Amino acid sequence: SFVEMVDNLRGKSGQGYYVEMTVGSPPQTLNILVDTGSSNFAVGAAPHPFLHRYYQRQLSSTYRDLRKGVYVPYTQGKWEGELGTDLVSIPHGPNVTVRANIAAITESDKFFINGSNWEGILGLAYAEIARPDDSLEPFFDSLVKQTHVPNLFSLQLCGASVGGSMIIGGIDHSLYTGSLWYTPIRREWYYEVIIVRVEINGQDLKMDCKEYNYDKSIVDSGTTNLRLPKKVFEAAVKSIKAASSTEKFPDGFWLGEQLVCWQAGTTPWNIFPVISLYLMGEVTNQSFRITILPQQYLRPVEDVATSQDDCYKFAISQSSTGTVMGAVIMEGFYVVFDRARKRIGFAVSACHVHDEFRTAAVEGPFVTLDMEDCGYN
Ligand SMILES: COCc1cc2cc(c1)C(=O)N[C@H]([C@H](O)CNCc1cccc(C(C)C)c1)C[C@H](C)CCOCCCCN2
C-alpha cells in the first residue's frame, strides 16, 4: 500500500520539502516541512505576513491545551509558542489518525519564508533533542505507539519546482536501483553517523578522520547545504578551487554569497570534482561510499538579471557544530531511516542526478581499519 505515498512531497529549491497534513476536528489542512534535523512538531497558529493560513485552535473540538510554553532555536531561525495536543492525519500517507503534541507558533524570527507554501514543521529525530525537554514525545514516536505502522520511514528527495516521496512505515522498491548500504545510527538524538574517509576526484583528503566528525555528523533534510567543520571545509575548498582553476570566480562565490552564471547550456560541469564520503558499515572493518556530483553542490538559482543564463550558488559551507549532510547530499539517493534496527540506508534514487560522463553512486564493500577511532568524544 506504499504506492499511495509516492510523490507526496513538494518544495521550492533551497526552501525544504513538505507534506500535506491535517490537524484538529474538523480537519484543517496545512503544508508541513519534513525535518530529520529536529524533533518538534509545530505550526503557525497566528497571523504572519508570510503565512497563507494557520492552525485555529478555537475551531477544533479535539484541541487540548497543555498550559506550558515552548521555544526552539535552530541554526537559522527561531520561534516560540504554546503547547497542546490534537488529532493529526496525513492524507497521502498511512490511513490512521494520531493524537500528537503540537507547538502552536505565536511569534517567530526568520523562520517562515516569503512565499514558501508551507506553514509548519515536522521534526522527525529523537526525543533527546526535543524542546522544552525530552519528555515531549515527538510525532513519529506517537505514531508508532498508537498504530501498527512499523518504526521506520524513507525519504526520496528529488532535485531541481522540486518533488519527492516520504514512505511512512517501509521501503518502496520502485524508488531505487542497486543495493541499499547501511550505516549505524551512532546515538539516538540527531540522526548521527560516522564518516571514516573523504575523497575528492579520487584523492584522499588525508586528515585524521576525527576531523570529519568534529563534533558530530548528522543527516538533516531541513538544511540545504553540505556543511563541513572549518578544517575540513578549508581543505575541500582548496581542492575544488584547484580542480576548477581553468576559470576564476569572485571569492564571495566560495563563501556562498555571490552566484555565478554561464551562457545557457554551457555550464562547465567537467571541471568540478566529485566528492566521495565513506561511512561506517554494518560488519567489522567494513565501510561503503557515496559519491556526490557537482550538479548536487552547485545549487541552481534564478537569475535576478535580464539575461537568461544558468546561474548557481556554491552549496558547501562552513560549520562550527559538526558535519551536516543536508538536502543537496540527500537528493538523488533513497535514504532509509531504519529506527527499529538503529541504522540508515543509502541507495541510488530513481530520480538520480545526471551527468554526461559521470554518475552518482553508492558502492561497497570497502575495508577500513580502526573506524571506531573516527568518532569524536
Ligand atoms: C548554511 O546553513 C544555514 C541553514 C540553512 C538552512 C536551514 C538551516 C540552516 C536550519 O537551521 N535548519 C533547521 C534544522 O532543524 C537544523 N538541524 C540541525 C540543528 C541545528 C541547531 C539546532 C537544532 C535543534 C533545534 C535540534 C538542530 C530547520 C529549519 C529552521 C527549517 C526551515 O528552513 C527550511 C529552509 C531553509 C534550509 N536551509
Image (cartoon, helix red, strand yellow):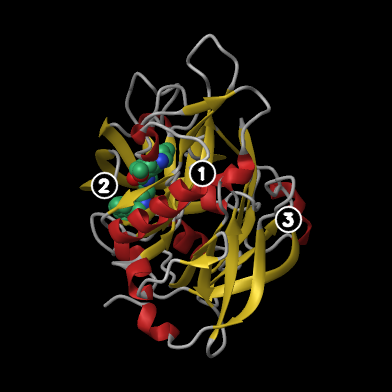
**Quadrant where the N terminus is found in the figure:** bottom right
Residue beneath label 1, please?
244
Provide residue 229's location: percent of width, then percent of height.
32, 58
Residue beneath label 2, please?
72
- Residue 182 lies in what quarter of the image? bottom right
Amino acid type at circle 2 is Val
Q: Is residue 199 above or below residue 241?
A: below
Amino acid type at circle 1 is Ser
- Residue 132 lies in what quarter of the image? bottom left
Residue beneath label 3, please?
2
- Residue 148 lies in what quarter of the image? bottom right
Provide residue 159's location: percent of width, then percent of height.
62, 41
Measure the C-alpha gap from mark 3 to mark 1. Answer: 43 Å
Label 2 beta carbon less than 8 Å to ligand 1: yes
Provide residue 154's location: percent of width, then percent of height.
61, 59
Provide residue 251's location: percent of width, then percent of height.
34, 35
Q: In this view, does 280 lie to the left or right of 354?
A: left
Q: Is residue 351 left or right of residue 48?
A: right
Helix, strand or loop at label 3? It is helix
Q: Please tell me whether mark 3 or mark 1 is closer to you in this view.
A: 1
Say which residue appears at 32% left-offset and 27% top-offset: 46
Say which residue appears at 53% left-offset and 88% top-offset: 285
Q: In this view, does 13 lie to the left or right of 177?
A: left
Which residue is at the front of the view, 14 or 267? 267
Say which residue appears at 49% left-offset and 39% top-offset: 16
The answer to whether residue 90 of the structure is visible from this angle is: no
Amino acid type at circle 3 is Phe
